Length: 108
Image (cartoon, rainbow, N blue to C red; front, top):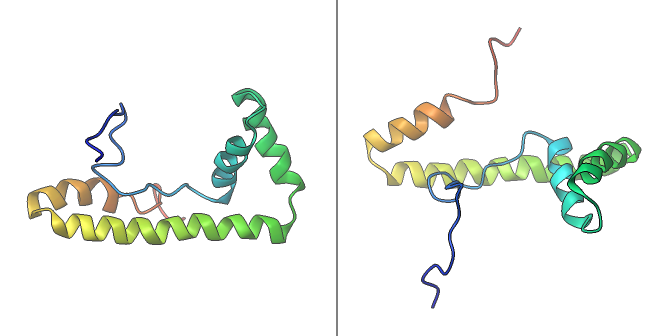
């Protein structure tokens, strides 16, 4: 059936699950650009800023669910995958992803 006709040069959908966006803002950016087929990446990126500024709270909240939702799946897809790999493997993945739980120098 599908023996991999073509490949990629990122290698993101193999080592780790679907990486969820940072927040609704960045998420909407990809959503708008995907719809803005008749708009250059330069206009799209700029549009996402305006379209996001005009969007109401109820509208922005909708995108928030998608972002958070992606995190839920990312955790599961990452968990089922991690456990699937040995300690050594889980260590590398855990020492790169688990270490970065969305934080900086300190909570402040």
